[PDB]
Length: 227
Ligand SMILES: [Cu+2]
Image 1 (cartoon, rainbow, N blue to C red):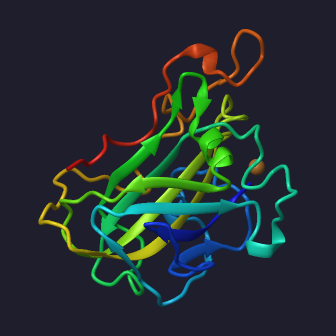
Image 2 (cartoon, protein in one colour; image 1 turned 45 degrees about the vertical axis):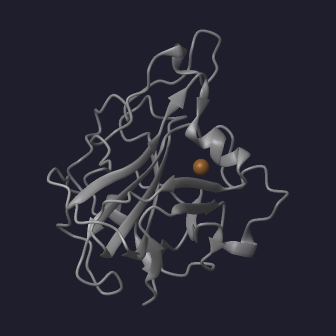
């Protein structure tokens, strides 16, 4: 149970919920065919569009509740340690990131982390105090994008619709950059199936721990767009 609530650009905190499309609470989306899978069930947004240089180190911050409603003492902040799973970021080119609707966009993946050497992306998130990072591709065309950030908690993912999707979107404007417009994109909903090997999955191993039995974890969705 967590909410995407801030972006940082090369270390500069952009502000609490600034440029963020956010849900009313920290409950997961569990229906991958719902429009909620795009940017969550959005109940607040603003007209701010964050400036993001191509090539910049982008941080996305997750907290158990909105801002002050989650404290440094909370064992489930940024998220409960049990909630093992991957963290991903997608972009979609839009006309105006502040005014665009979210249906029918063409999404491409720019970052993902799953399971490696016994450690999940969520473990990194906890180690880094609620922040997850990626480098904005250098070659991407400048301008308005929606940035979809996603954390999938898999501690109850062995059952249908048991995977817990924590999602939000940020409104961004990429500066500098190149001319790349990814030819292969995906739809939300559409990109995920409830039967995907990284969504319908029992992550508990031989000794009952969340180690996925040491097996490779297949992060849902497409290959990364790269420069
Ligand atoms: Cu939870």
